[PDB]
Amino acid sequence: DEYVQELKGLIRKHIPERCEFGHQKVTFLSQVHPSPLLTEGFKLLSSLVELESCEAHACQANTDQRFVDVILSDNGILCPTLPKVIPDGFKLTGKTLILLETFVRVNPDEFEKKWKADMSKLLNLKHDLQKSGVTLVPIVDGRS
Amino acid sequence: VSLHEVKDFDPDVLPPEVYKELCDAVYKSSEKCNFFLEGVLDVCPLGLLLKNLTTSSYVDEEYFMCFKYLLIQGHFDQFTNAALRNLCFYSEDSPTEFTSISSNSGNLKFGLSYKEQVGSNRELYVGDLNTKLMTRLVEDFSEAVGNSMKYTCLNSEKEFERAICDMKMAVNNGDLSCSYDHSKWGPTMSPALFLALLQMLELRTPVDRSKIDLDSVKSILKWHLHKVVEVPINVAEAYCIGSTSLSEEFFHQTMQLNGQIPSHIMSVLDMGQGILHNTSDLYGLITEQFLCYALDLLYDVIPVSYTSSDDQITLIKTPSDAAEWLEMICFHEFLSSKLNKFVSPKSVIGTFVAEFKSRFFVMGEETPLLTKFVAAALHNVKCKTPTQLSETIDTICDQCIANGVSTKIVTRISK
Ligand SMILES: [Mn+2]
Image (cartoon, rainbow over all chains, first blue to last red; front, side, top):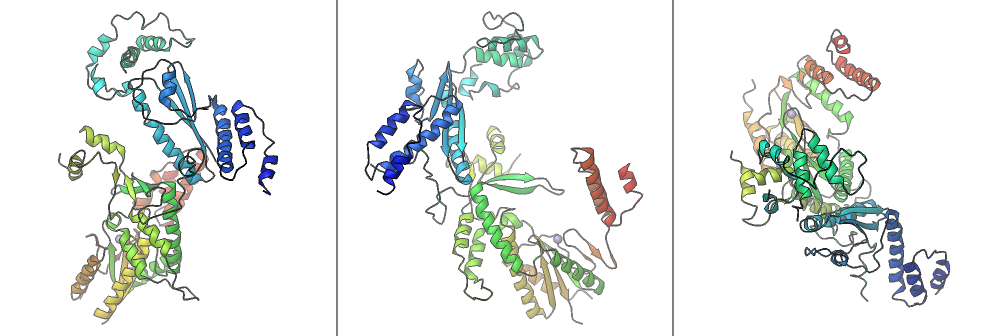
């Protein structure tokens, strides 16, 4: 392992700003096997990117990766049988919801492809939640 | 009031043409205790915004805003690595495996639009980024091939000047002129024609004679053949909401008789105008060269042609009074119609006036084209600051005085 332990040593320049940062850090450091480390390294990098992007905009990080139905049912709100979708960042106030789905694409073409796909899959949900429920405002944060 | 429930639920799109104005005026002035408040309340703290908006709309003359504010106040609106690793930042839609009909990243989706012209509205096609780059590499390859070509006149001013001077000498000599205008050039051609043409060709190298294989060109041309175009929505509400029309009949046959509402159009022969200009240019050029070679070998009369991918001009140099050759002209028309090059009835095939790119040439001189330039000068006042406007007027007046209009007129334009 010429670079594995090298990576472990050099990833020590990270600030555990949030609790989940340390929670994933300790699991990554306590697991050295060929099959996982790439997967959880990619997921921790993506979590860091999405955390920066969303607490750029008054975030409430989704540590459970649950659906919109359960978070809407956490308080007293009827279920309109909403289609399933996993949100990245949610902020509900009164009877309003702010939805943020972020991503990263180094090439433009894929960037607008993902932007259009996300915009389309977030617009269709408003037609169902407004009929017998509350609103939402979809915001998309795309980083090149 | 309740009809919004069965119909669309958006209160901001309710049209005023369904209800009378008297009922709207009298209804908003009814009893309302907790829906209005005293005073304008310019401070507008949070929590009472609807009441302030209703008061501001009511104190004004308009009541439709008051009516919709009342409506919205009343609450009438009630461990694998291939599936679990494609949601964080993985670019699953990257083009890695492609078929003859797609590219694993879409289907070259296009949008239809218009562009105003003097005669009739011109088609326009707008492409997404991926299909734009694909058609644009096709464009680059085709301009390269046409740059290798000699007789084309689309982007080479030297050949355009050569055609102009040949036309002038031809008119001065008594040459036979054929100004061919092709009808429905855009919506008639199909990519499959280009597929066959490039399959049958060889495209030999200059020194290597290696017979370049255009496999990527063939695959991308098949992609273009499998492009899908999205109909503008405005016509969708225009036809759905609801004179006999064929397209309206097709829409009325295809909302629920076969499937859902039509939103994406897919067919064989489109050749979107503004997308495959130069490939069609080279195809037309080589076909016209074949036709003129055939005319030379059959009627022993010497042809030359110039093509601009939409219209062409052919000069016929004659051996050895102009009524003995209708037959070869009908024959050429027939052979062109055998190809996908239908000729519009606007073509004139005599020997007194020649046309190409709206630049007429007559025996002795050239038409000045006065009123066209005058009208162009009077129009297109592209105004941002007076200085740029003076510059543009100067350029247009220079262009106008170039074609011998007058100098007592440019003074009036300046005034
Ligand atoms: Mn013409």
